[PDB]
Image: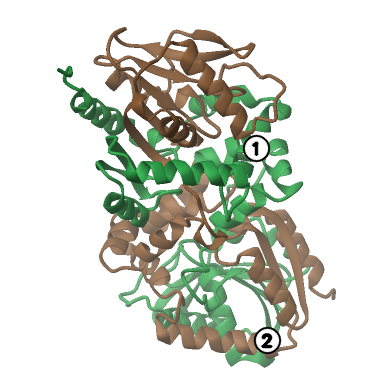
Chain colours: A brown, B green
Amino acid sequence: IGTGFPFDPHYVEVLGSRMHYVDVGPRDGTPVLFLHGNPTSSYLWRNIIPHVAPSHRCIAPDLIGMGKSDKPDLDYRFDDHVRYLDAFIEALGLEEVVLVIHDWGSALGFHWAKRNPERVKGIAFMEFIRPIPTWDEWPEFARELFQAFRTPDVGRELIIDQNAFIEGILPKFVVRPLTEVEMDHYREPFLKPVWREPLWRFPNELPIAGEPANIWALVEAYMNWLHQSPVPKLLFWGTPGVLIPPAEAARLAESLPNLKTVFIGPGLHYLQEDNPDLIGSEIARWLPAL
Amino acid sequence: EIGTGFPFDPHYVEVLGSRMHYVDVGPRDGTPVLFLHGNPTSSYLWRNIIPHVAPSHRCIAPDLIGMGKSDKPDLDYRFDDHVRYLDAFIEALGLEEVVLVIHDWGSALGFHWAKRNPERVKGIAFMEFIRPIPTWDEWPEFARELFQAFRTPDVGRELIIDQNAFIEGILPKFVVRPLTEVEMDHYREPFLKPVWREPLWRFPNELPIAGEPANIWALVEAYMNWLHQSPVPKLLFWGTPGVLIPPAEAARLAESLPNLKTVFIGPGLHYLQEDNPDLIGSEIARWLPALHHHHHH
C-alpha cells in the first residue's frame, strides 16, 4: 500500500481562508468529489484516486482546519464545515458531481446531496454517520466479532488457521505499541497451527448470556463466593477496558468486601503491558510486610 | 522503557506426566504470590510486574498446560483440563497458603481454586477478569465507553487535545493492517500543536446521539430520510468487523436503501481506505460508467 502523496497542490480562496485540494483527471465530464472525515485529510484517498483519475476528474479537499487547509479561528462545528465546503464547491464552479464520502465527510456529502439532489449523480460511501437514537444502539463492532470467535467454523478458522488472537487481539488490546521482540516471545508457543487449540477453546467457553451453561454455573458460583468472602481483594482497572467496563468496576466496589481498587489509566485487556510499574508496585504495597 | 526480555531462569515440574514451566524468584519461607496468565499469553505477561513484588515475596508464575514453555499433551483443552493441571501444579510445588494475582482465564482458574480452598488464599489481586456477562446487548461496551468519554466535559478534551487520542489512538487502532511510521507522520503533520486539535474534539461532540445536539440530529435524520426515498445510485463499501457499520448493519442497509449496490472489502475497521484501497478504487472506477445519463431528447 502506497505511502506517498504524489499530487500537485491546489488552493482556492473560501470565506477569506485558503483550502487545499487534490485536482487530477480529465477536465470534462462529471467530477468525483472525495470527502474525508476525522482525523484525516485528502491523504486518506491517495491510493484510491489513481484508479479513478484515468477516466474522471477527482477533487479531494482538505476540510477547513485540517490537512494543508488554513487554520482560522473557528469552533469547527459541523455548521462551520458546511459553510466552507459549500463555498469550496461553488468556487470551483462544480455543477453535477459524484460523491465518495466517509465518516464526517459522509455527513457533509449527504447533507449537501439532500439540499442539492439534482446535482448528485451517484454516492459511494462507507463507515458513515447516521442518527443513533439511544446510547444502547451505539455500534459495538466487537459484538459480532466476539460472537464469530466463539463459533467452531469461522472462529476456529480465525483463531487457529489465521492465528488471529496472537496477531490481532493481543496487540490491538494493548494501548501502547507492542514491539517485534515482544510479539516474537508471544508467538513462540504457537508457531504451528496444531498447537493453537487452547487459543480457541478459551473464548468459546467465556460465560456470556448464560452460555455455555456449565461455565456459567461455576463462574456464577465463585462470584457469589467472592461477594461473601472477607479475603483481601485488589482490583486493577483501566479505561475503556474490555472484559471489565468501568461501570462493572464500580459495581464491584459496591458489592465486594475488603476491596481496594487501583485505576491504571488507559487500558484495554492486557493491562500488564500498559502500566506494569503501577500494578507491580501497588501489589507490593498491598501485601503485608514481614 | 517497558522491558522486552524474559530474564528468569526456567524451572520445570512434572505434572500429571507432562512438564510445566514456571518462574520462581524471591525469598523463601513466606507466603508465595502465584501469578496466573490467560489467553494467549504466558508467564511472559508478568515479566515486568514480578520485579516489584520479588524484593519481599516469593513469586511463582506457571505457564498453563499447552501454553508458554509448558508441554502440549493431547487434551481437549477445555476449562476442566486447565483446572486439573493447575491443581496438580500447585500440589507438586507443595504450596500451602498463597496470594493470587490473576488475569482473564487465569482469573477463572484462580477464583475457582480459591472458592474450593478458601483457607489457603490470603488475598486476591485481579484485573480484566472473568465474571458472568449478562447479555450481548450490554457487552462489549468499549466503543460506547470511548465515545461517551470524548463527549464528557474535560475528559474528552484531555484525551483528544492533550493526548492527541484521535491521531495516536483511534486512527491506527481502526485500521486492521499496521500503519507505517511514514503514514503516521503524514497524518500527524496538521496536528503537531495541541491547539490545532480543536476540530478533532468538536467532531465526536457533534455526533447525533439520542437527539443531541438537536441541530445535528435534525439534519442527519433529514438526509437519511431523503436517502431512503431517493433513486440516486448508491454504492456502500463495508468491512469486517467494521466500526460504525458492522456487517449486520450493512446487511440491513442492503435491504432498505433504494438503488444500492454493496461491496465487501474484507478485513476492515473504520478507515477502510487504508485496508483495501485497490478494491475500493477499482470498484468505484467500474461503477462510474453506468452513472452516465444519455443526452436527453
The answer to whether residue B115 is above or below residue B226 is below
Residue under pointer 1: B202
Residue A144, given in percent of the width and then of the height, sits at 39, 61
Q: Callout 1: residue from which chain? A: B
Residue B166, given in percent of the width and then of the height, sits at 59, 38
Q: Nearer the viewer, residue A149 or A107?
A: A107
Give the secondary structure at mark 1.
helix
Would residue B91 be seen by someone viewing this image from the given angle? no
In three-dimensional space, the C-alpha distance between marks 2 and 1, rounded to whole angstroms, equals 42 Å
Q: Nearer the viewer, residue B14 or A142?
A: A142
Looking at the rendered structure, whether the residues under marks 2 and 1 are on a common chain is answered as no
Residue under pointer 2: A227
Which quadrant would the N terminus of chain B be assigned to in this image? top right
**Residue at the spot 71% in from the left edge and 61% down from the top edge:** A279
Q: Amino acid at mark 2?
A: His
Does residue A142 appear to the left or right of A54 in the view shown? Answer: right
**Crowding near the residue tagged with mark 2, few <14, some 14–19, many ≥20 C-alpha atoms within 10 Å:** some
The answer to whether residue A261 is above or below residue A222 is above
Residue B112: image quadrant is: bottom right
**Residue at the spot 53% in from the left edge and 9% down from the top edge:** A12
Q: Amino acid at mark 1?
A: Arg
**Crowding near the residue tagged with mark 1, few <14, some 14–19, many ≥20 C-alpha atoms within 10 Å:** many
In front: mark 2 or mark 1? 1
Q: What is the total number of numbered labels drawn onto the structure image?
A: 2
Residue A182, given in percent of the width and then of the height, sits at 52, 48
